[PDB]
Image (cartoon, rainbow, N blue to C red; front, top):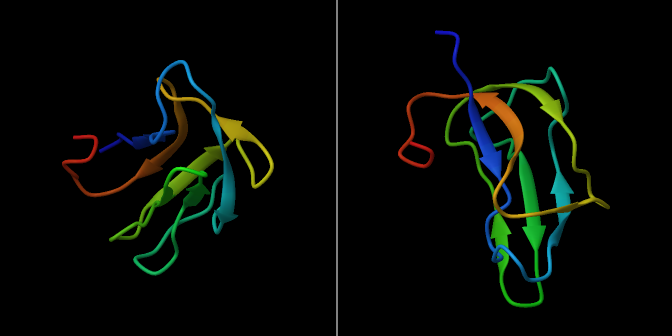
Amino acid sequence: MGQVVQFKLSDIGEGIREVTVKEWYVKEGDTVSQFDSICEVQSDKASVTITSRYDGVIKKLYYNLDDIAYVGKPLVDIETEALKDLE
């Protein structure tokens, strides 16, 4: 009801190098699907992919395939069923 779950860069530590998005399959104001992942980042250390597992509404996206995200702050807000992930 009116609430959205936000995804934040996770993979690196709060002080080390940041990571860029390798795959983007969503846009601001766009909806996601179980097959349509939101953002995917890959680092020399490990590769992380963010799936949906459900259909949600994405309102804004700041980081792109070229931009780097930092741990400690959300990057995108999406509406999805209560997930342990964020919650």
